[PDB]
Image (cartoon, rainbow, N blue to C red):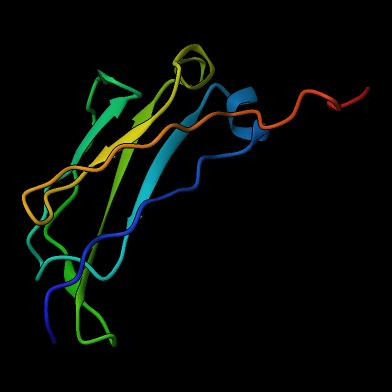
Length: 111
C-alpha cells in the first residue's frame, strides 16, 4: 500500500489515576509511515520532560505499521501544565494539539 499520514489520538487516564499519584498519557499512531517515525512529547508549546522509551513499530493486519508513545510522569503535571502534544516524524512535518483534564465548568462532580 501507499504512504499514509499518522492520526492524533490522546487518551489520558482518569481521576482514579491522579488520586493515586500516578498518570501516564499515551498517543495512538495508526496508518502512518512504513514503520518510520519518531517518539517525542511536549506540553502545549513548551517541551516536556520527555521520559518516553518506546521501540520500533510493527506491521498489522491492515498491511501497514503502527506506533505509540507513552510518557510516564507525575499526575500533578497534567493539571499543572497547559496542554499535551505528541510529536511524530511523518511527511517531514510535526503535529500539535491542545489537551486538558477537565472539559466542563457548568457542571462538575459532587460529594
